[PDB]
Image (cartoon, coloured by chain):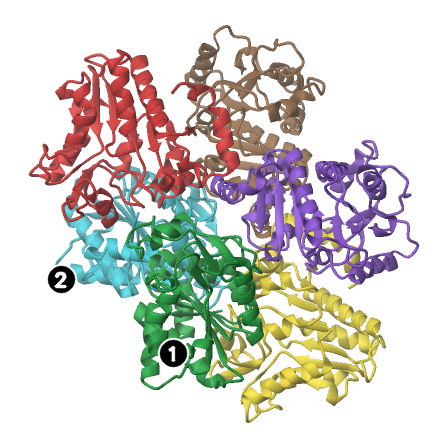
Chain colours: A cyan, B brown, C red, D yellow, E purple, F green
């Protein structure tokens, strides 16, 4: 695993964005061989999407041959509602880059047959073969996407009943109304995430401290899903300063020294 | 992983039995595509076999196209001895259901060539392809079948020298005589168990408390084999109240709330 | 996992050597089907190479059809320098056995194109298919070869910048001069090691106590690479008395009783 | 230590109040030998003060010869401000019982010489000799009164700079304004608390779960001050259900069985 | 603390007995200044009483001026019943030594007023001033005498309701009848024990392994009363080999080396 | 407890020295009421003695009425040998300050009757009443002075057989000869140290990291003597940066923020 210890969210975004850009340019995607990118929504990926857009406008990347798959979507919320994941993604990323519509994959929270919808999402991915880089965040309890703790490390895209905590936390977007927030959501599984060739988790804020610690210093265990990324062939944790509160001083010094060359510039 | 927290052994049996029945009816086994079931012996599976028989008599399941493979057998004990696993299985299950004899697989504790016997057991399984649901119990130290702690998570069917503790614990069936109890036994390996598509462990009694805790809350480690089920794609722990003594109050509250819909009726 | 608890390094060497010899004679290698052996250098493997040579001279083994792959080599150090791994290997093993030169694989610390060199090493291995037995040691922090803690359990042969600690520790061979010791080295990855059919780690000295404990009693975690051998299908830890200082009295008693038959003679 | 596990805050209050009443009636205080009571303010002691008042009105206790000492007070906040501890105490307790004004001891957050004020508070206590029963609550981090974690277990009454967390948490009383909340407060020390003959901590809410666990199951350590009550001669933890989330199922079952006789009625 | 690691119970007894004898001869007790000895009953102290008697017959000690206080007694069991602690003490010790009857203190399980009985026991001790050496054993859960886990480290002589586990364990003396075994017992408190100038705990059997570990390696905590002896000015743990199963190999090696001079002979 | 986290040893010395100076000037010692100071020798106290001397020369302190007691001395080493603690103390401190010879207390490693020597040292201290500030260091294993781990927290001045590790570590002063280093030493006990009104431990170097962690974050336990300072009424840990390697990032941030005002200047 790699731990990129940075100070700010702006830095994390720049670093994460640059890593994606580099992976893409090195892959050199074509129409027959696109670079498949897994993506998250929310406040965490904010600075990364912002950096990605900048680099693109600076002419450093083209998403012309990048295929994206998003982690989740609200069930029963209309696509153009400003708080659907589809809306967040276009407003924050797609509206400013050259990615073709056929290359954008998002779950249909309004599909009549949910199981079929999820099943097909999994199928669309396999049709491409594999996701080259799946970017995501982590819950305060180490959970991934809408997967609950103790999820099978082999779980797949499926619908989930949002937890009270998730509700309140998102009630703010449904303007502080936890009553507004949808009841269910469609989410990729942990297996879906782990099948990615490379996984990059964005860790921001002191409230992620315990999860960062479980991921980096703790032992592999299913209650803290994030900890199983220790078994993944290519995982990276990109974090800010506040999130490092639960790590030993030496652990942080280790990675800060080991990755010093890679964090200059961002 | 799933944790079905129930109060009694009778409930655990009803729940476990119903799960097996459901898996079977949904699979809809045929002569060319049978449902393969892994099975344990002993006091733990008692209420489950009892429930399975009831459901069958109630006309809810047919084992006409179910192929079973049992975890173990005593070496050098004659099949019709009432304390062989073969005898336990027929008396408690096979004598009351419609499973054909060719569909019943049990290790031959009397095979002249033991290694060959074990080797062939492994081969018979692969011939079918895979076990769809392997039911079992767990040792007080988290061990599986006759496998000892620190067994390779890839171990296979082989003969084992029973431990003093196992002897005494079973001496009761050889009527409190630990002297009667056989010295060796043939047991499926941990790899054999993990290759099952789904694994369901029955946990009964306060003496399993530490193992349940190692399985659910602890970290993955080989000393407590049961803990590695955390890495399995589809594992379920069905337990009674006494076995939950070592879990945190919140851990138990979590699963009790998460599985409330699934435990009504049994 | 297996833990062979012995008293001395001489015993560990005899045991390890005998195990290799046995694995070879049982495999019965030919020109078209050689036995592939992974090997380490350093003070730890000393008594084993010494025992291996004895057994060979005693006519108990022939390495005529054994192909070996070594874990590492210093970058930019000339092959005949007495402190290169190539020199250690010939002086301590190859000079006294019947292994053909084409069967000896060592990394070229002087290859003009390092990445290509490493890439090809990985390719040479796959050409043979798989390593049947990879012998190695472990760092005081549980690390393997020149891989650093938190290495991906899927890492591959690559060049590494030696750590200050490694320098000092080896400065003695570059006659107590840490200034002499080379800056980089080529090392097989953890994935390379884990792909071995069987892995045997030599643990000598009280300074390995914590690592032995992490391997045997601890939970699976990437900071202590050695602990992930718990997930390997066939791992053995052969150790001396001083290295057992951090194990519980009962843990050591367990393995000492479980392996009593296998440690008589050595 | 004693752990009274109850379900609700109302029960905790009834139990705590009854214990105080009983201690008083058994002591049978006089003008020359009063019963000295240590007291806390805040939402936690709410139901207890309510129960104490009821019992008094029911004619079950008289505070005519009870001397009270309160844990803290805001510095620089006028006594009659409705949010001073003096105001909370009279409105919630003193206004409804027969305690004489000379028997009420509260720190003077407005004393011109703070050190002298604190010094004298400590002196007033010793003049009486000892506090017979000190009731209090506990911070989410196990801290006591306004004492910070790692306070000397021998600390004494002194002024403290309130922590941001304390501010926000109390900003609600200064009507959600954290800006209103005073900057410093006068608080009894941990030594002051431990010198009490008997200490009774009220634990309500899931946010106290970790502290309850540190107090009951954890080891003695100064970071979680509450844990040192394990060394106190007569400590009791009276708690509600939510606060028990971090305890083992068996720990809670132990105390629930051990104190079953004492919790009927309340 | 001191840990005397011996191999057998016979050795533990010889060592413990010799220590008592030495403490006595060095004190040189008189009629006005007797040596006060705290004593336990049960299978654990067996070899010690046997050794003490031998040394006395060998003319190495006289108990003419030794005053003894025993830890407990069954409530409502007649003194001459062969299973009362009074009977165990005379049959195993007093019947063979020169201690005067007025120097023997045992709790009166038949006192009409129990609280008074206990109160007076505490008073008799203080009249002498202090117990010079209190010998005892430890429960499998680290508890002392009939004190339950989480007892105040300042508890005193009082009556206790025996636990089911204690019953069964002692049912053997009431000839395997747990129905025979008395319901309550009078026991000295933990405070009583800790006030002893020196405390010596006899630890025999693998079932005490966890408690020995909690006492020697664990942290101070009230759930394992024995662990608080770490805070006592003069505590010694005399143990046999089986009881050391939970200690680290190095911990045992430490004390075995530190006390090598003191364990030759016994 | 207090933790003064500084960057360098020079800072630690300045801080420690300033604290001593302040304690003295505030006490305002006289001929009839001197300030009693406990002192350590070795490399750790180096910068502190250097700072103390500076402040004295700067006219900020007079040791005219300061009585000092040193922690230890080598047995059988002549006082004027340059490596005796007496020599270290004069050369590094006494030779440059105004302390009278009658105010200097050092153990006599050459006393004919050692027990008497130690006994009297303890008596000299009590004659003064109490040590106002005892400064010291800590072993890599948390031990204090020459006291071994698991020492009674009530131990007293006595002779000790130096450990191999202590030998080697000090062999450097007996010019790298571990053969030169004396075999025994006289050391104050842990009780002696804890009786000090205030205890200040100097922690320098990464090798003290584990001990600093045991002192600050760990639980109270006798194996790490330093951890029991958590129970002391007035303890301070003054440390440098390297020694903080084992602390959590947040723990260090806590004290760095809590003591920011007190570490400016030094």
Question: Could you say which is closer to the camera, residue F179 or residue F247?
Answer: F179
Image height check: is C61 above or below C216?
Answer: above
Name which residue lies at 68% across and 48% down: E143
The foreground one among E65 and A43 is E65
Location of mark 2 (residue): A58
When asked about the image quadrant of residue A238, the answer is bottom left
Expressed as whole percent of the image width and height from the top left, the position of residue B122 reads 44, 17
Residue B113's x, y, as percent? Answer: 47, 7
Given residues C88 and B238, the one toward you in this image is C88
Tell whether D246 sits left or right of D45: left
Going by the image, does D211 lie left or right of E116?
left
Q: Residue F18: which numbered mark, if any?
A: 1
Q: Residue furthest left?
A: C112
Q: Quadrant of the C terminus of chain E?
A: top right
Count of numbered marks: 2
Q: Is residue C18 above or below residue F40?
A: above
């Amino acid at each position: 695993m790699r731990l990129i210890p940075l100070t700010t969210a702006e830095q994390v975004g720049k670093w994460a964005a640059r890593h994606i850009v580099n992976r893409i340019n090195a892959f050199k995607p074509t129409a027959d061989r696109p670079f498949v990118l897994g993506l998250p929504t929310g406040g965490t990926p904010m600075t990364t999407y912002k950096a990605l857009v900048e680099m693109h406008k600076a002419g450093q990347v083209s998403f012309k041959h990048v295929v994206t798959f998003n982690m989740d979507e609200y069930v029963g919320l209309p696509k153009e509602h400003p708080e659907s994941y589809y809306s967040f993604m276009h407003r924050n990323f797609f509206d400013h880059v050259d990615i073709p519509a056929e290359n954008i994959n998002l779950l249909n929270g309004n599909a009549p047959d949910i199981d079929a919808e999820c099943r097909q999402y999994e199928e669309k991915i396999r049709s491409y073969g594999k996701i080259h880089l799946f970017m995501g965040g982590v819950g305060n309890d180490g959970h991934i996407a809408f997967n609950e703790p103790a999820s099978s490390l082999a779980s797949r895209t499926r619908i989930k009943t949002l937890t009270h905590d998730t509700r309140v936390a998102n009630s703010r977007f449904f303007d502080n109304d936890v009553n507004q927030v949808p009841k269910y959501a469609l989410t990729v599984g942990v297996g879906t995430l782990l099948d990615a060739e490379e996984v990059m988790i964005l860790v921001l804020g002191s409230q992620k401290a315990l999860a960062l610690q479980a991921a980096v210093e703790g032992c592999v265990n299913h209650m803290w899903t994030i900890s199983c990324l220790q078994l993944h062939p290519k995982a990276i944790m990109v974090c800010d300063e506040p999130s490092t509160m639960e790590l030993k001083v030496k652990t942080l010094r280790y990675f800060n020294e080991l990755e010093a060359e890679n964090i200059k510039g961002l």
